[PDB]
Image: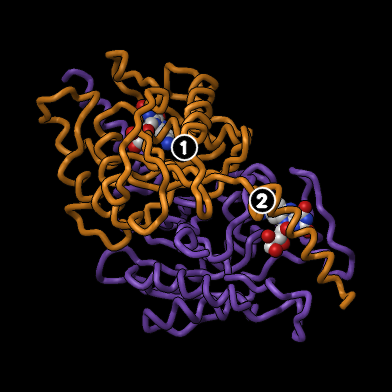
Chain colours: A purple, B orange
């Protein structure tokens, strides 16, 4: 060997650590709901629990078309109308009913508590619901969605979970032992983030991809 | 309707603007890891440190090129490595673009590049002889220089595809978030897409590591 053998063996071991090329790995496709805030200032419904906007329906259509060829074996959503509506667009193309877990709800906000929203500096946690509590309920909800999905006989078992920006960012940061502000990202509306799961190991595979929106105005 | 929705929307808009969303003059850089070049490397008669794509890699590059065929792209860049240039060519061929090369997009220098055996390190332990700060700086300057060499798109967002390498890309994206090796604890899949937003000299990580075009792929491809 000229060094390529150890290179290949180390590469294999690194991949295995991150659940690449490992049998028995399932995937969770974490999806942020579609737009529900264009026109919110004039909305006659509950502004904290709005339906999708016209723009959001278009984003959900682009997301559903992106996922049409992806095998999906379950679809879960929070109880929020904007998540349910986004999930319905995906689930219909895969012959699945949307299932609901309120543990997927967005972090409780100042607005929920009647206090004005506040722009915080980077690194400063902006929500009244503690990060640790959000991380725990999100991890429990995602573990339950995985456990609820019977293994598919073809390929990778995959469950879609439609939720909310800050709760999803907290979940993914938590899985990397990072706190709020370290994974410094806002997840786009209809973005897809992927976790790889095997027993007790939950690996962040990809984060925040909304590339299906690029060809649309 | 003075019920908090106006405050919520204005703060949301400010948060978005901090991450270059809804801001004029923003370009996108779609960072792509090259396709497979390591299947069958044990038997390869070429330069094993600069391999061409494998048959698997050509199939992955085909899926990637089809995924990006409908995305407006205004430039395609690659490192000088055959595996990156070949992947970039597949992408660029769907857009009428030439592949532009920048050697600063090369992978981190490895033990193998030095003729030394490779070693599996614990998580958080930097495994390469080229320092992380040097990798981050050359990647950051290569990306901004590619944008500076791209004429702004006449309609909508200017978008440059950049084909590179796992560890250098992870180091770039971690560094843009002020994170060191091991904090952004991820391996980027072959042909994965990661998006940066760029305005002037500022670069924001928008998405990381998506290889969802391989989600349905068979065993002779995945
Ligand atoms: C990186 C990042 C920072 C955010 N900063 C704030 C913030 O400073 N104040 C706030 O009310 N909400 C925030 N949020 C929540 C967002 O402003 C919005 O509520 C989400 O994009 C969904 O509306 C932040 C979320 C983030 N992801
Ligand atoms: C999260 C992460 C950890 C890695 N650990 C090592 C390592 O412990 N030893 C090594 O030689 N190369 C490594 N690497 C380098 C990767 O094995 C190379 O980037 C492969 O080409 C990616 O498959 C690491 C890269 C990673 N991304």
Q: Residue at x 25, y 59 (%)?
A: B217
Q: Residue at x 76, y 66 (%)?
A: A108
Above or below residue B116? Residue B125 is below
Chain of the residue that carries numbered disc 2 in the rendered image:
B
Which residue, given by chain and number where applicable, does mark 2 sit on? Answer: B23
Instruction: Work out how far the residue at label 2 is from the one at label 1, CA to CA, in angstroms.
Output: 19 Å
Near-viewer residue (B99 or A70): B99
Near-viewer residue (A13 or A115): A115
In the image, B128: left or right of B12? left
Q: Tell me which image quadrant ligand 2 sits in.
A: top left
- Secondary structure beneath dot 2 equals loop
In the image, B98: left or right of A196? left
Q: Position of residue B87 (x, y in %)?
A: 28, 41
Q: Crowdedness of circle 2 by 10 Å Cα count: few (<14), some, many (20+)? A: few
Residue A133 visible: no
Label drawn at residue A188: none
Q: Residue at x 60, y 44 (%)?
A: A177
Query: Is the shortest distance between ligand 2 and the CB of mark 1 under 8 Å?
Result: no
| 2 and 1 marks on the same chain | yes
User: Marks 2 and 1: which is nearer the front?
Assistant: 1
Which residue, given by chain and number where applicable, does mark 1 sit on? Answer: B150
Q: Position of residue B119 (x, y in %)?
A: 35, 24
First reached walking from the N terminus: tag 2 or tag 1:
2
Above or below residue A190? Residue A22 is above
Quadrant that contains the N terminus of chain B: bottom right
- Secondary structure beneath dot 1 equals loop
């Amino acid at each position: 060997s000229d060094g390529r053998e150890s290179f290949l063996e180390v590469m294999r071991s690194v991949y295995e650590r991150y659940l690449v090329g490992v049998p028995g790995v399932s995937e969770v496709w974490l999806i942020r709901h579609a737009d529900s805030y264009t026109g919110l200032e004039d909305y006659d419904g509950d502004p904290r629990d709005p339906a999708l906007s016209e723009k959001g329906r278009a984003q959900a259509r682009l997301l559903a078309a992106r996922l049409a060829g992806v095998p999906l074996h379950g679809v879960w959503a929070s109880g929020a109308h904007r998540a349910q509506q986004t999930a319905s667009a995906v689930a219909a193309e895969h012959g699945l009913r949307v299932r609901t877990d309120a543990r997927l709800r967005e972090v409780r906000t100042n607005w929920d508590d009647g206090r004005p929203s506040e722009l915080k500096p980077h690194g400063v946690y902006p929500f009244p619901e503690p990060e640790k509590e959000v991380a725990e309920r999100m991890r429990t909800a995602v573990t339950a969605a995985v456990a609820a999905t019977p293994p598919a006989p073809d390929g990778t078992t995959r469950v879609a979970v439609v939720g909310h920006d800050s709760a999803l960012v907290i979940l993914m940061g938590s899985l990397m032992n990072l706190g709020w502000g370290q994974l410094d990202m806002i997840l786009p509306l209809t973005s897809v983030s992927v976790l790889a799961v095997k027993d007790e190991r939950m690996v962040v595979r990809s984060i925040g991809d909304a590339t299906h929106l690029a060809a649309a105005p």
